[PDB]
Length: 66
Image (cartoon, helix red, strand yellow):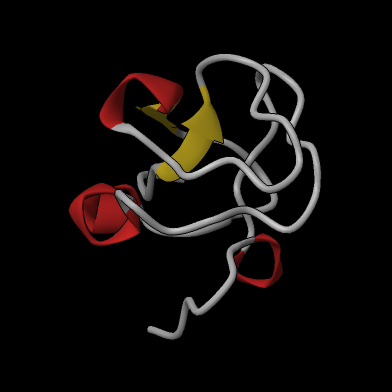
């Protein structure tokens, strides 16, 4: 396990536009969106509430493809 994923550094309400303070990088399982894509995610919207500490998955971000 060396691949880190993006996880929620705070509760992100449904339909929020993602900012950099909201995302940390952490080695978690299952693996979600790669931590190196945190720059690609700023200004995109999530389509559900993401509690603090939850791994961000591809299907949670509106318009994400990678």
